[PDB]
Image (tube, coloured by chain):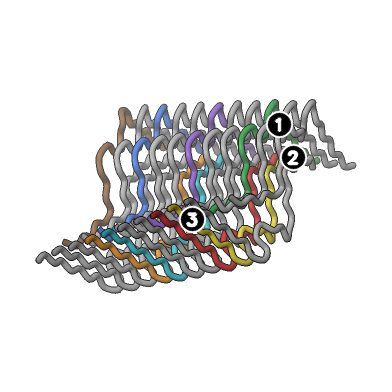
Chain colours: C orange, D cyan, G red, H yellow, L green, O purple, S blue, U brown
Amino acid sequence: HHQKLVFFAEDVGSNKGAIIGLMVGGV
Amino acid sequence: HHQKLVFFAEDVGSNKGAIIGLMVGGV
Amino acid sequence: HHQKLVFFAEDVGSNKGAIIGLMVGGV
Amino acid sequence: HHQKLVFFAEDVGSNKGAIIGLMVGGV
Amino acid sequence: HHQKLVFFAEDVGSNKGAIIGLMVGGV
Amino acid sequence: HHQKLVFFAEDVGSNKGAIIGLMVGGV
Amino acid sequence: HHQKLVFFAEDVGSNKGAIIGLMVGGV
Amino acid sequence: HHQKLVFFAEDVGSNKGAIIGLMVGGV
Amino acid sequence: HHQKLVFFAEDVGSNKGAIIGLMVGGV
Amino acid sequence: HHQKLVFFAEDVGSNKGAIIGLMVGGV
Amino acid sequence: HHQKLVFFAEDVGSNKGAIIGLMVGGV
Amino acid sequence: HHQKLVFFAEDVGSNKGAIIGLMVGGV
Amino acid sequence: HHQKLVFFAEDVGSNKGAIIGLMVGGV
Amino acid sequence: HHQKLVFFAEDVGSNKGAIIGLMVGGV
Amino acid sequence: HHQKLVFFAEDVGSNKGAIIGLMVGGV
Amino acid sequence: HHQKLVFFAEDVGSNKGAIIGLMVGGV
Amino acid sequence: HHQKLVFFAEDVGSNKGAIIGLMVGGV
Amino acid sequence: HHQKLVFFAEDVGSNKGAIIGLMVGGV
Amino acid sequence: HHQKLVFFAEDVGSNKGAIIGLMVGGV
Amino acid sequence: HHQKLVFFAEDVGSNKGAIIGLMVGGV
Amino acid sequence: HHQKLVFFAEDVGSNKGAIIGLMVGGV
């Protein structure tokens, strides 16, 4: 037999800030 | 027999802020 | 026999903020 | 025998904010 | 025997805000 | 034997806000 | 034997706001 | 034997707001 | 043997607002 | 003194395809 | 002194296809 | 004195494809 | 003195593909 | 004196592919 | 005196692919 | 005296691929 | 006297691949 | 028999700050 | 007098691959 | 007097690979 | 008089591999 159990609680993996992939800027 | 169980609670994987993929700026 | 069980809760994967795919700006 | 069970609760995968695919700005 | 069960509860996958596909602005 | 069961509750997939496909603005 | 069952409850997939396909503005 | 069952409840797929296909404006 | 069942309740696919196909204007 | 001038050329704001406001279907 | 000038050329706002407000099917 | 000038050329803001406001389906 | 000039050339802001506001699918 | 000039050329801000605002799928 | 000039060329800010605002999938 | 000048050439800020704002998947 | 000049050439800030804002997977 | 068990607590793997993948800047 | 000049050449700030803001996976 | 000059050449600040902001995995 | 000149040739500041901000993993 094979078993795998996963539990993510209240506020897992959430974004409350800023995620920027790529930023290019002149002056 | 094979089993896999996953539980995502309340507020898992949510976005409350900013997600920007790509940003280009002149000035 | 094969089983896979998943649960998602109240506010999973929800966007309450801003999602921008691509942004280009001059001045 | 094969089984797969998924449960999405109250407010999963909803948008309550802003989703922008693409944005271009001159100034 | 093959089974797949899905349940979406009260307010899944709904839009309460803004969805913009594409935006172009001169100024 | 094959089965697939899906349930969508009250306000699933509904729009209460604004959906804009494409937007072009001069000023 | 093959079965598929779908249930949409009270207010699925409804529009209570604005859906605009395409918008062009000079000013 | 093949079976398909669909149920749409009260205000499913209804419009209670505005649907605009295309919009062009000078000023 | 092949079967299909579809049920529409009270106000499925009803318009209780405004639908505009195409709109053009100057000032 | 206040002036506003707008010019629309040949096939501006025209439909040469399909515009559907709302669509519902069981199967 | 106040002025507004608007010009429509050949086929502004014309429909050369299909415009459907609302469509409910079934099977 | 105040002036605003806008020019839309041959084929601005036209639809040559498909615009669907809302779409609900089953099985 | 105040001036604002905008020019849209041949095929600006047009749709030649598909624009869907909202899509719900049972299967 | 104040001036702002904008020029959009041949095929600005056009859609030739697919724009989907919202998508909900059971299977 | 104040001046701002912007120029957009042939295929600026156009979509030729797929833009999806929100996607929810059961399986 | 104040001057700003911006130039976008052939194919700036365009999408030729896939932009997905949000994605939730059960399996 | 104040001046700011910006030039974006052929294919600046364009997406030719995949942009995903947020992704949640059960399995 | 093979078993693996994972429990992630209230606030595992969440972001409350700025994530920037790549950054380029002039002067 | 004050001057600022910026030049972005052919393929600056583009995406030709994958940009993922956030990713949550059960298995 | 003050002067600032920036030149980005062919393929500055582009993404040709994978940018992941945040990744969470249960197994 | 104050002067600053910056030049970035080639694919300066580009990503061709994998950028991951944060990575959390079970077994």
Where residue L21 appears, as percent x and y from the top left, is: 63, 48
Which residue is labeled 3 in the image?
A: H4
Q: Considering the numbered disc 3 on the image, is that residue within a helix, a strand or a loop?
A: strand
Which residue is labeled 1 in the image?
A: L8
Label 2 to label 1, Cα distance in Å? Answer: 9 Å
The answer as to whether the residues below labels 2 and 3 share one chain is yes
- Amino acid type at circle 2 is Gly
- Amino acid type at circle 1 is Phe
Q: Is residue O10 left or right of residue S15?
A: right
Where residue G13 appears, as percent x and y from the top left, is: 57, 59
> Which chain does the residue under circle 1 lie in?
L
Judging depth in this view, the residue of S16 and U14 nearest the camera is S16
The answer as to whether the residues below labels 2 and 1 share one chain is no
The reply to whether callout 2 and callout 1 are in contact (CB within 8 Å) is yes
Which residue appears at 44% of the width and 57% of the height? G4
Label 3 to label 1, Cα distance in Å? Answer: 51 Å
